[PDB]
Length: 218
Length: 218
Image 1 (cartoon, rainbow over the protein chains, first blue to last red):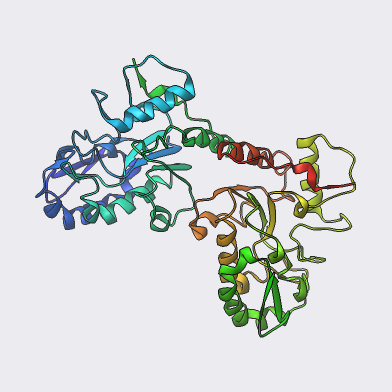
Image 2 (image 1 turned 135 degrees about the horizontal axis):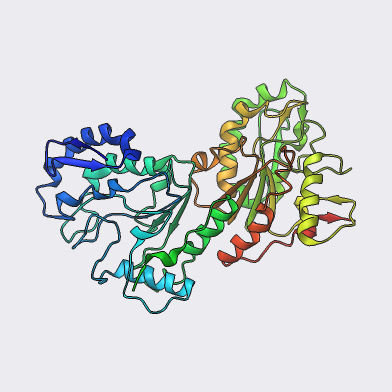
């Protein structure tokens, strides 16, 4: 694992070699915007912005993408809630509980599932303000997601309003599903069948399915 | 059913009201390119270019799409071979035979199946030359398929090279599967499960399945 330097906090970014082709562009873009975004208190903290760049991409076939980190308590790992309190990962875990039949569990983590890379489109938000740093991450976000979609075969985005312009933004040939947000009203995420549709699409493309039960913590 | 006039052959285009929102753009685009198309002898003939615009779209949930008409003997109805001689429709018929269990039949037509709209991406070719009018239909082809994908739940494209970047060019939320071309080598179309999976995907989207046996002619 290499690292590069940036002018502002967190000053160094360590990354898995799979990310190498985008890193010089990332440094340039981050140096342009970091001084502005860092004036706000952020979720996650600056030292955690880029920790997901330590994940390999070549063993990944599905990206599960939310728009930005949790308003509060972001860890730098997308969707991760160590104490299992965040609504999104609780609703996701319930959806997978119904799919797989596993009813007794203490937590759920999208970051421990073979073939899945969980992702936050924007890498920070001003503390307590969802989507507040969209203007800063803009170009970086497109750069990094485009790079992810060169490896994965299915991109699954959560939030129809959040990602209403994602296909025009990405100009990608990759299969893209935009489902309901886990906190969508009228219980619409509970009736969402995107987790099931992903595996059907993978198996048609001669890829192994995702074992969604791997995410459970007991 | 309304009609609209164009400057060149076939001079008048009759269309089902479901197509209304794209027809003013179509006449504009066709008037720009029709002279280029019409210098060549074509499959189909100019009076058959647009007959598929007589099909309604609101009762359609699957589009089955090939890149252009048969190099010769195109009827204006995509995939249609009245005498059942064309390799593509014969291979399709054979795949649907293995799926449904119907073994005795004289022909197959994708244009007589409830919920299915068969489609040719480019609406003509120079006689005997596949993809020879790609450049002329370009913008019309994008316009018309984008309109189809606002109505249908599943877009099934045949030909992995032909349709490699179709999802990028469409920027559509429709479920798109790109399978082998019926005449592909190493029996790759015979082993293609796409027709089978269409109904699995429709059920997941709370849609009725396709009765593929409706296409058979006895």
